[PDB]
Image: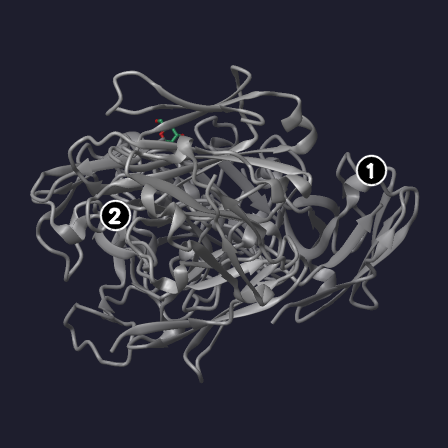
């Protein structure tokens, strides 16, 4: 069927280089307007570049001279060479077929490019101890603070997955230091603070760090 | 068919000097005006110098006038940009391009860059 | 440059409501406008082109109107799969080829529920490292419009706090919010009263949870 | 006789850019001061010639091309430019010797509901050669399945209509463009100044 398959994204330092590839089926790249669209974390959509069927290439002002769009008809694949990468370029990159007034009808699944503005750092886990100020009668709240890690993602489980109800793992936030922070909380009975072992299991694959922290009451 | 390749850039200190070169091919070099352009990270591409095909008429931007010299060798196919008394504001990727000079009913020579670009050369002043 | 704006930013509606999202243009763009739908983790899907024509495969409940500076995307009967973020896109523009709007998120309407506010003092382990972080938690509340105001010795604090909000829960369609105020150990020791003031539509008056340093 | 620039500049309706009109100018006397002394032109750029010295010159071949485009595409009517108009509708040569004249026509070519008579070629497989006109209406094949005159997926009409409305911004407003081509060769002249 018709489909655009993207690949070629990862983590890279500022001034680095990477090449995105958008393999196509059900349409001919060399005969269509082919565009790249990127979506920054938590932001909207922005056009990046477009290649015409006649070969003319147009780029956004923020990427002109650094990014190069190209295609290979023998492989029916659309390319996006990204050089001199900066922190502005971290986003999910989408390849799409442009029909001008008829819009962008076919899209690819997307490829994440995270330029390494900060070094790959493991997370420091700090306990959010339950207390009277965190007690709601018969139910109490506790959790762990996962701070100063790069890049995404981090996986947090509670009691090796044995505790799921009441678990709220919040979306990550990027601090001013360029490092991500996250908090996972769980609401548990106040009478179980002295009988049940509450442990948060934080795993950060890029840094190969696995931390299990027991959240203790009082 | 037109091919433009820039060279000569690098790391330079304020008050220093660099010579840029642009090898051209795929067209009649002497029949087309040429110009140097630069784009700094975060700002739009800006025109630097403009030189006629014969090289008898040269024009410069106010920010580089008295510091940058634009020249060409039509025997070869190379365009030159001699930059003197460099300052940190000159840090950018410098491009060479063909350009068409147009005149208005009351104005003089005005430049329009051909939308064909090479890789450019990096000049960092610090 | 022509600026594309969308109103509202967050829309709450139930299944079966008529939902109208407006996209505005700084200058007249005739019918050069397209509508897209994006779900979390999913690539955008085209819904309408030419500001009125419906793309093949799109349900008839989606409709587009307007030409010039004001455009609207109308859903006659909101369906459970229509809860997503919707973008408008100016077409055939200059200098960029096309420009996308800010986007509008459609979420499930539900009875107003007040948040359960919990405060967490910084741990001794993080203190020994030289940093202090205090966390305020808002659990199972609706609507998502909840403000957290950090107060240090009754002085409102800004610029050193960050917030995070969960997506609508699968079971009860409620949100959860976490606010983290980060200070250094030296500045943390310089103050005593740390408070988290929360206003929400379910609260008639703001509710403040607070602790003194050293408890 | 005077050259028929009035029948080109002052025509009631202009041609679409995909089917741009060409009026041959020959065996007449041209007073170009009617153009360069007017303030009704938003664009007046001459390549290889000076606008003030046109009345003092003689030419062997003169052509006048006219079409309607958008305001954001007047820049593409120039040597070395790229875009939908330059690549697929009207291409100027790199060694162009002539003048490009444009003026806003919102009060004439824009209708309240939208004038959809002016068209541009949207889909084409190859860029136009300089001074080339393509008036084909064949269905464009975007994939590998032939269209055979039926419009659908990967099968689109090559011509799309401008939406010209008075509420449109200056970029989307219609602009009437006249391109004058001057050819100076070692041959007897046909068009001269008074
Ligand atoms: C078009 O008509 C106006 C008004 O009559 C006139 O001034 C102008 O010279 C005409 N243009 C040409 C090219 O004759």
Q: Is residue A83 left or right of residue C3?
A: right
Chain letter of the residue beneath label 2 in the structure image: C
Circle 1 SS class? loop
Residue A122 is situated, as x and y percent measured from the top left of the image, at 60, 58
Residue C3 is situated, as x and y percent measured from the top left of the image, at 40, 35
How many residues crowd around disc 1 within 10 Å: few (fewer than 14), some, or many (20 or more)? few
Q: Can I make out residue B123 in this image?
A: yes
Q: Which is closer to the viewer, label 2 or label 1? A: 2
Q: Quadrant of the C terminus of chain D?
A: top right
Residue D155 is situated, as x and y percent measured from the top left of the image, at 22, 70
How many residues crowd around disc 2 within 10 Å: few (fewer than 14), some, or many (20 or more)? few
Q: Is residue B45 left or right of residue D88?
A: right
Q: Can I make out residue C22 in this image?
A: no
Residue A96 vertical position relative to residue C191 in the rendered view, above or below: below
Which residue is located at x 61 percent, y 40 percent? C124
Instruction: Please tell me which residue lies in front, C146 or C151.
Output: C151
The residue tagged 1 is B65
Instruction: Please tell me which residue lies in front, A19 or C52.
Output: A19
Q: Quadrant of the N terminus of chain D?
A: top left
Q: Which mark is residue C169?
A: 2
Can you tell me which quadrant of the image ligand 1 is in?
A: top left
Which residue is located at x 39 percent, y 45 percent? C93
């Amino acid at each position: 069927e018709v489909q655009l398959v993207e690949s070629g994204g990862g983590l890279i330092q500022p001034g680095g280089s990477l090449r995105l590839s958008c393999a196509a089926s059900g349409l001919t790249v060399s005969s269509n307007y082919m565009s790249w669209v990127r979506q920054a974390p938590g932001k909207g959509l922005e056009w990046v570049s477009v290649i015409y069927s006649g070969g003319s290439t147009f780029y956004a002002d923020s990427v002109k001279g650094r990014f190069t769009i190209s295609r290979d008809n023998s492989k029916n694949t659309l390319y996006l060479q990204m050089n001199s990468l900066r922190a502005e370029d971290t986003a999910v990159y989408y390849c799409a077929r442009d029909l001008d007034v008829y819009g962008l009808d076919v899209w690819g699944q997307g490829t994440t490019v995270t330029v390494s503005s900060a070094s790959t750092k493991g997370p420091s886990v700090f306990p959010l101890a339950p207390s009277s100020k965190s007690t709601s009668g018969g139910t109490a709240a506790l959790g762990c603070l996962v701070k100063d890690y790069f890049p995404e993602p981090v996986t947090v489980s509670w009691n090796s997955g044995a505790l799921t109800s009441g678990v709220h793992t919040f979306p990550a936030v990027l601090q001013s230091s360029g490092l991500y922070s996250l908090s996972s909380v769980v609401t548990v009975p106040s009478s179980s603070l002295g009988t049940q072992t509450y442990i948060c299991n934080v795993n950060h694959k890029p840094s190969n760090t696995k931390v299990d922290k027991r959240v203790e009451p009082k | 068919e037109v091919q433009l390749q820039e060279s000569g850039g690098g790391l330079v200190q304020p008050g220093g000097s660099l010579r840029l070169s642009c090898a051209a091919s795929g067209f009649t070099f002497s029949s087309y005006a040429m110009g140097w352009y630069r784009q700094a990270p975060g700002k739009e591409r800006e025109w630097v110098c403009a030189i006629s095909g014969s090289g008898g008429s040269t024009y410069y931007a106010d920010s580089v006038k008295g510091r940058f010299t634009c020249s060409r060798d039509n025997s070869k196919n190379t365009l030159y940009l001699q930059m003197n008394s460099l300052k940190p504001e000159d840090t950018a990727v410098y491009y060479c391009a063909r350009q068409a000079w147009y005149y208005s009913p009351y104005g003089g020579p005005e430049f329009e860059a051909f939308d064909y670009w090479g890789q450019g050369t990096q000049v960092t002043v610090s | 440059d022509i600026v594309m704006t969308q109103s509202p930013s967050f829309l709450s509606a139930s299944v079966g409501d008529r939902v109208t999202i407006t996209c505005r243009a700084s200058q007249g763009i005739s019918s050069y406008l397209a509508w897209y739908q994006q779900k979390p983790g999913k690539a955008p899907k085209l819904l309408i082109y030419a500001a009125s024509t419906l793309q093949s495969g799109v349900p008839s409940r989606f409709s587009g109107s307007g030409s010039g500076t004001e455009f609207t995307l109308t859903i006659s009967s909101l369906q459970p799969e229509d809860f997503a973020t919707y973008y408008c896109q100016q077409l055939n523009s200059y200098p960029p080829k096309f420009t996308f709007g800010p986007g509008t998120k459609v979420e499930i309407k539900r009875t107003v529920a007040a948040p359960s506010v919990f405060i967490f003092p910084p741990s001794d382990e993080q203190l020994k490292s030289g940093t202090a972080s205090v966390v305020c938690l808002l659990n199972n509340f609706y609507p998502r419009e909840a403000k957290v105001q950090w107060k240090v010795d009754n002085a409102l604090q800004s610029g050193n706090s960050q917030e995070s909000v969960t997506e609508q829960d699968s079971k009860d369609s409620t949100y959860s919010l976490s606010s983290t105020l980060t200070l250094s150990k030296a500045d943390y020791e310089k103050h005593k009263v740390y408070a988290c003031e929360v206003t929400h539509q379910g609260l008639s008056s703001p509710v403040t949870k607070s602790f003194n340093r050293g408890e | 006789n005077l050259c028929p620039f009035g029948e080109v500049f002052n025509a009631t309706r202009f041609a679409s850019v995909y089917a741009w009109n060409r009026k041959r100018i020959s065996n007449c006397v041209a007073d170009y001061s009617v153009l360069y002394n007017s303030a009704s032109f938003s664009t007046f750029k001459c390549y290889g010639v000076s606008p003030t010295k046109l009345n003092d010159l003689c030419f062997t071949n003169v052509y006048a091309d006219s079409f309607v485009i958008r305001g954001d595409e007047v820049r593409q009517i120039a040597p070395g430019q790229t875009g939908k108009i330059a690549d697929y509708n009207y291409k100027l040569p790199d060694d162009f010797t002539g003048c490009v004249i444009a003026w806003n026509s919102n009060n004439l070519d824009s209708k309240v509901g939208g004038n959809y008579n002016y068209l541009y070629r949207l889909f084409r497989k190859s860029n136009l050669k300089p001074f080339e006109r393509d008036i084909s209406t064949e269905i464009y094949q975007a994939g590998s399945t032939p269209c055979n005159g039926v419009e659908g997926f990967n099968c689109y009409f090559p011509l799309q209509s401008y939406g010209f409305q008075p509420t449109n911004g200056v970029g989307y407003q219609p602009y009437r463009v006249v391109v004058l081509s001057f050819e100076l060769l070692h041959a007897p002249a046909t068009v001269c100044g008074p």
